[PDB]
Image (cartoon, coloured by chain):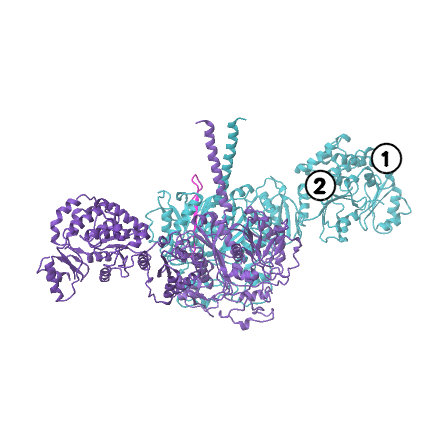
Chain colours: A purple, B cyan
């Protein structure tokens, strides 16, 4: 190597490090911050951003009379004379419809604590839940994450007049402390990021935003919850501002109007969720808009404590613009404060003229509007409201008109032409030019805040399962009804709805599942759930306390087979079909026919009548069903088998390889077929059975305290059956052409060992509770002699299930094409002194051997706490927007 | 240039850019922050950090009973039964001594507003002023600066139990709003940095500190004010927590003690001043310690809302250590949040053992303590209080012992030995190993904060003026008493105290000044000021309203000469001697003597009798004094001269060069000598004298409405004197051998014009209000013809004085070795229509011409609003620490 190239490599490394350093500096200074969702409670029964957008664009108001359910004494409160004390001269204001409502149980709050709680905190809890739901995130997924909370909240004298009542738990404090406002959100959602509650007058919310941005840029918080709340429980503010004559007589905020005369106050709660743009892209979240820069400062020594200052506003605007490295011609509109104050509006307009309006393009003037003209003035939640207005304008591509600007104030020389007020709705559609806007807030204390916002960057008939959950039956019914209403539209994408329910919603104790192929059946089932009568077979429900289980796979013996089982699954399940094909190829150098042909009943294959064909086929089917179950996230904890089912279990446990299992099954099946028409079996008190059997010499298996199977020669079998039928319980016969688990087996031992003395077991990965020696077994112990013993000795199913049940296992999934052992398992569990909320489920049925039946089985399991990865059932689908949780509210108010 | 050299240049630029970028990254992330000043108000009459240190090191307690001056109904309040409602079973706690006191006038707030004010805000104002003064900074110097304010404060209920009245200004709302708590600090001090108030339970202060550090690093603020306040207006907290039995029976916080049983509450306010270390070093501030890193987080879904969580504490400790890049072995002591709670303390100790205690060196176990055990609980200001104690420990190099630790708690295991409690004071002298400590805060809301701290980096008999000022006479006397007591100490430094007063204190309305050379004269003068009798000589007082003045310079004519004038100045003033020496050099090729000889009265120098020597000496002295005035920052707005004085003025203004002025003055002096013993002058209504003069043929000047000057031949002079003597007012004579401003002069006209025709005047940088033509003149017009006319035509001194007076000028300075026109100027301004507070002052006196007299003259000027740059008088002196303002307090309290 020469000197020049050695210098060049150093230069290249230095340049790369320089680029990385510049990237880090940009990340720390002006990293773009995205917005993922938003939520709001606002006057006039407004609780969705869509409703607010409709109101704004239409151009309505929410002003109304005083509330009447808050214990206020309206009689003495009203008086015409402003000078009269303890009275106000206005009777119009914004208010919330149901501020007294709350659902204590959903948040695990006792009634007394709920009553002691400030309504603000309750509304923040509800709005935070709805916010996290809207973004498309499971609320439970945030437990244990660096998520911050930043709120602007202040006390409004709630419950002070309430006579001191006994309070052992100190509810009196935690219900009114502003810090607890965000502390309780963090506590309930389980967040670990910083929790802060600021109070800087009416600009609090934006202040809370600014801090949050820094936290997100310092890599200290992954997500931020930013917003404000204002719910006045007493009329004190009205009286105080009436003393100063700072209230509009009619109660309207006429921003920049000739008749501006004061404030129109209102309540409201608002929240937004913030994350880094790059992290939003990486996680796949959706983006509504982007934040670029912000600026804060103080008016300083102004003319009076509460008077505004123009120079401070100009300085903060310029700082905000320079921080993000933009120019004043880059902005298109401003959501100015505009509280309708007589003295303030001209100042703000002049500042805007001097900062943006100067040297403005003659054709592209700055559009100026105010949201306070419509919704009023919420103080603590004022700025975030303007931000939300800007976001809605961006999404809908339109600029709502601002009200009461028919006659602009003469004090601002609009002849300059740099700015213009939105007298009517203006299209703001996307195009080559970038869209940007600016939001402002000016606290009475003197702090000012200015923020810049920019547009976001440019961007079959198979079975469908649907899951729904809630914490109460009424809530579950309401949820089902809401989903039904949603699905009745022609636009709904059934797969999208299913995926959204499966992945973007939390799982509560009350659960209900519906598998459907068309929307009509789905809505029918949802109506059944809402009405409380789940008669249909496509609807299941349940209630559970634990989100997990200890799953066990049961592998039964004969009886489950039936012609055509698995035909549909072959075409519908690539995993199952692949397992069957693999088993076919593995079994290939032992025989001619293929299980794949047998299932389809193709031309030229044996039927399900000879042992040598049924046993391998059942083995293959059962293994494939086990693979399918595992595919959906259900990894077994232990495996149990019945007779040759043990083989399959061993293959599932990993102790054996597929080829060895095929050899074993083929061997045993052929050597058993060698005994065609030489023995029999029948079904049925173990001791009583043995005593009755003594007279002869011909016990096979034990399935419970009363279920018993007997085997042996035909003649003695008939003799015993005749006696038993003449004494009591029936003797049900079995379809088989031999006698198993009997001395008859002794003859064929040597050939079996000759054939199968070459298998090489392995260590196990899943507990293999053998039914032969009744204990956990090491994979090494399963040799040819073990399988001879398994074939020879008696079967102990009841004992195995009992040992498993009292060991802490509570879920039992029999892997078979038909339920034949569920009943015995249920009876044993009931007689067992183990977990009482056990769940037992089959896999398929004699009929309905299609994917839908398997999904119904999985839903029956899921509604009982077993985890399922429903997303697997919905390949290629995209999630869909859904409504929020239907809270069941009650009244909680502390009255004097 | 070879390829290698160019590649080397590219490489060098890349490397330097990379290094600068890494520096920028470090500045943004973990730039060290310095502490410059601190202030506190605490129980037991503790109002200074020094008192707190004394208390802690001695190991005292401030516990006391409930206040009796807040209106609380004590009889009903106290009761033993815990469950009896509306009563408290604890009767001891920490309280401030003068919560109700406040100085209203100083902060410019009316008594009614102050009464409506929350005491917290008042104490915040006082403590903020004291904090800014302690740093060694003029509070008025922060006006128009980007200084942020961050506080942790919450409401307690001042004013709810009173009746609403006429509040036209909104005092009821403004007084109690927490946002206004910081808004008022910003407003009164004229700061433009962000003002933010937070509430996060007991950890609010450290959260504010974290935010302030972030803001300082971002460059958003130049300096930050951080701290908290907690004043208990009503006994709600006590009764409330009594309902829960959460309070200690004795009210003593036995942190980490076997007897810990609950809380003990106290009131307190604390503040600290922060700025980047490099900025403090560059500006030259004092550094008390360095803050390195901090971390905030939340308990998350802990065991209950109010319960603590150890894992969160460990996480925040690790984040705090990692933020600045340190190791647990680098910390020598921690100040826990030990509140004396049985549950909490073991958890915190266990968390500490797992982070610093793990793998800890066996010869330096981490020292553990808690300040709360001494001053109880401070709630909102708790965190910052701990930070205080550490800093003091750093400054004094000692760790105070902790109280109530006679028997450590058994729940925690100290056998590990990684952590040890501070049973007794431990020497902590500065040495090779760096000293570091940590502070912790855990709020009930669930927010946990951790911070790290490090020690700061390593580092005649002339006259002296002492200045004092205040907004009230009583405050001024109190200040003077404080300064005298400071000087009475043996360690007191005179120059340091003088400079500290000059540069580190704001200048207020009422002012006083004492010039002294020894501490004895100083202390006596201060005592006389404190007595209210300014009878002494080296003491001046006054009251001024404006901080500036339109100053004017006055140059009198003959009369101010005397023997020995300027002897002390030649030695005690380099500027004066330099200017006079320059004049001598400029004067060399016209004469032989040096004016220095005449002033020193060196042998062989002409006496002050011959007119050919007197005038140039006055010229030189006047220009030298003008330069002396300039050097102290007293720049003249305009100049005015009497007779030859204009020449001097012309040099001060800049129209004439020193050499040219010497030429003109020497020529005039010689031509006047040429007419020795041929004329006379005498002093004296202009009309009354003009009507008298008609008979003869000889008027010289006009000094005022009655003061007039006459010149003429000896015979007519004596005749006029005889006539006026037998008619009334006297006629003073003048010592001179000629007649000036008369037809006599016309003889020597042409020779004067020829000799002095080489001058080349220039534009004048300062207004030159010529008295020859009664208006301002440009320099270029001042030719030899003009100067001949000056020597010839009458003077209009009074008219010039009046015109300058009514034109807005208010301060007149007579730059001369003796005042000869002070009375006339004072009268002239009296009958004018300008400012009524015009100040007039001389420069020296016949009796006394040393630097001290000139300083007294400048003090007489300064006490009337004229700015002076005193620090020039105190070169090299190191500033000295001084006490803060002596607030005069009155009771303001809203009673039920």
Total count of labels:
2
**Which picture quadrant has residue A803?**
bottom left
Q: Is residue B139 magenta?
A: no
Q: What element carries label 1?
A: helix
Q: On the picture, is B601 further left or further right than A722?
A: right
Q: Which chain carries label 1?
A: B
Few, some or many C-alpha atoms within 10 Å of disc 2 (few <14, some 14-19, many ≥20)?
many
Q: How far apart are marks 2 and 1 (CA)?
A: 32 Å
Q: Relative to the observer, which residue lies in front, A447 or B734?
A: A447
- The residue under label 1 is B750
Find residue B65 and report its horizontal and vertical position in percent.
45, 61
Q: Which sits earlier in the primary sequence, circle 2 or circle 1?
A: 2
- The residue under label 2 is B626
Please identify the dominant SS of the magenta region: loop
Few, some or many C-alpha atoms within 10 Å of disc 1 (few <14, some 14-19, many ≥20)?
few
Magenta-tinted stretch: B428-445
Q: Is mark 2 on a helix, strand or loop?
A: helix
Question: Do the residues at pointers 2 and 1 share their chain?
Answer: yes
- Residue at 42% in and 40% down: B433
Q: Does any portion of residue A377 appear in the rendered image?
A: no
**Which picture quadrant has residue B342?**
bottom left
Q: Mark 2, mark 1: which one is toward the viewer? A: 1
Which image quarter holds the N terminus of chain B?
Answer: top right
Find the residue positioned furthest to the right: B695
Find the residue positioned furthest to the left: A695
Find residue A627 and report its horizontal and vertical position in percent.
29, 51
Find residue B427 and report its horizontal and vertical position in percent.
42, 44
Q: On the picture, is B191 further left or further right than A845?
A: right
């Amino acid at each position: 190597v020469t000197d020049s190239e050695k210098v060049a490599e150093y230069l290249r490394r230095a340049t790369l490090d320089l680029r990385a350093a510049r990237q880090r500096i940009r990340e720390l200074e002006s990293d773009p911050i995205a917005i993922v969702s938003m939520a709001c409670r606002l006057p006039g029964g407004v609780n969705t951003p869509q409703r607010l957008w409709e109101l704004l664009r239409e151009g309505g108001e929410t002003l109304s009379g005083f509330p009447t359910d808050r214990g206020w004494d309206l009689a003495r409160l009203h008086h015409p004379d402003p000078d009269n004390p303890g009275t106000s001269y206005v009777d119009k204001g914004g208010f919330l419809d149901d501020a007294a409502g709350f659902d204590a149980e959903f948040f695990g709050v006792s009634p007394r604590e709920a009553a002691a709680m400030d309504p603000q905190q309750r509304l923040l809890l509800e709005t935070s839940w709805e916010l996290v739901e809207n973004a498309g995130i499971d609320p439970h997924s945030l437990r244990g994450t660096a998520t911050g909370v930043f709120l602007g909240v202040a006390k409004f004298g709630y419950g002070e007049d309430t006579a001191a009542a006994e309070d052992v738990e100190g509810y009196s404090v935690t219900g009114v402390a502003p810090a607890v406002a965000s502390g309780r959100i963090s506590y309930t959602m389980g967040l670990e990021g910083p929790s802060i509650s600021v109070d800087t007058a009416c600009s609090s919310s934006l202040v809370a935003l600014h801090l949050a941005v820094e936290s997100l840029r310092k890599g200290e918080s992954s997500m931020a919850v930013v917003g404000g709340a204002a719910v006045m429980a007493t009329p004190g503010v009205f009286v105080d501002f009436s003393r100063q004559r700072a209230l509009a007589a009619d109660g309207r905020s006429k921003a920049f109007g000739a008749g501006a005369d004061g404030f129109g106050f209102s309540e409201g709660v608002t929240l937004v969720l913030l994350e880094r743009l790059s992290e939003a892209r990486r996680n796949g979240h959706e983006v509504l808009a982007v934040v670029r820069g912000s600026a804060l400062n103080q008016d300083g020594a102004s003319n009076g404590l509460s008077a505004p200052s123009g120079p401070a506003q100009r300085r903060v605007i310029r700082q905000a613009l320079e921080s993000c490295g933009l120019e004043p011609g880059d902005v298109d509109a401003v959501e100015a404060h505009g509280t309708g104050t007589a003295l303030g509006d001209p100042i703000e307009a002049n500042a805007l003229l001097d900062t943006y309006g100067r040297d403005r393009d003659a054709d592209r003037p700055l559009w100026l509007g105010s949201v306070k003209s419509n919704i009023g003035h919420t103080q603590a939640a004022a700025g975030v409201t303007g931000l939300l207005k800007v976001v809605l304008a961006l999404r809908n591509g339109e600029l709502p008109a601002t009200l009461h600007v028919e006659e602009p104030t003469p004090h601002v020389d609009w002849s300059s032409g740099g700015v213009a007020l939105l007298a009517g709705n203006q299209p703001w559609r996307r195009g080559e030019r970038t869209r940007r806007a600016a939001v402002s807030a000016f606290g009475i204390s003197g702090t000012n805040a200015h923020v810049i916002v920019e547009e976001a960057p440019e961007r079959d008939g198979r079975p469908v399962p649907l899951v729904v959950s809630a914490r109460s039956t009424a809530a579950l019914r309401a949820q089902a009804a809401q989903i039904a209403e949603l699905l009745e539209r022609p636009d709904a994408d059934l797969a999208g709805v299913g995926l959204g329910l499966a992945t973007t919603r939390a799982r509560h104790e009350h659960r209900a599942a519906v598998v459907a192929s068309t929307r009509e059946e789905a809505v029918r089932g949802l109506r059944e759930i809402a009405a409380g009568a789940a008669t249909a077979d496509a609807v299941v429900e349940g209630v559970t306390e634990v989100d997990g289980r200890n799953v066990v796979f049961l592998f039964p013996g004969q009886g489950s087979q039936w012609a055509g089982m698995g035909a549909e699954l072959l075409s519908s399940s690539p995993v199952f079909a692949g397992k069957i094909r693999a088993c076919d190829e593995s079994m290939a150098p032992m025989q001619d026919w293929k299980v794949s042909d047998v299932l389809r009943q193709a031309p030229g294959a044996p039927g399900l009548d000879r042992v040598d064909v049924v046993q391998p086929v059942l083995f293959a089917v059962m293994v494939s069903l086990a693979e399918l179950w595992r595919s959906y996230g259900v990894e077994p904890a232990a495996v149990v088998g019945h007779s040759q089912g043990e083989i399959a279990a061993a293959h599932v446990a990993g102790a054996l390889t597929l080829e060895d299992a095929a050899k074993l099954v083929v061997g045993r099946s052929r050597l058993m077929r060698s005994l065609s028409g030489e023995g029999g079996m029948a079904a049925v008190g173990e001791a009583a059975v043995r005593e009755r059997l003594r007279p002869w010499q011909d016990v096979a298996a034990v399935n419970g305290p009363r279920s018993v199977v007997v085997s042996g020669e035909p003649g003695a079998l008939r003799a015993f059956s005749e006696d038993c039928a003449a004494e009591g319980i029936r003797v049900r016969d079995i379809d088989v052409d031999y006698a198993s688990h009997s001395p008859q087996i002794e003859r064929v031992r040597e050939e079996l060992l000759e054939t199968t003395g070459d298998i090489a077991p392995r260590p196990a990965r899943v507990t293999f509770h053998s039914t032969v020696e009744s204990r956990s077994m090491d994979g090494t112990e399963l040799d040819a002699r073990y399988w001879y013993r398994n074939l020879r000795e008696t079967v102990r199913f009841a004992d195995a299930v009992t040992r498993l049940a009292e060991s802490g296992y509570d879920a039992f999934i029999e892997v078979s094409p038909h339920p034949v052992v569920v009943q015995a398992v249920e009876e044993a569990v009931e007689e067992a002194d183990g977990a009482e909320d056990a769940v037992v489920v089959g896999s398929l049925h004699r009929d309905g051997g299609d994917l839908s039946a398997f999904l119904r089985s999985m839903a029956t399991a899921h509604v009982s706490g077993v985890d399922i990865r429903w997303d697997v059932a919905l390949p290629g689908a995209a999630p869909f927007a859904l409504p929020t949780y239907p809270f069941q509210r009650k009244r909680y108010w502390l009255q004097p």
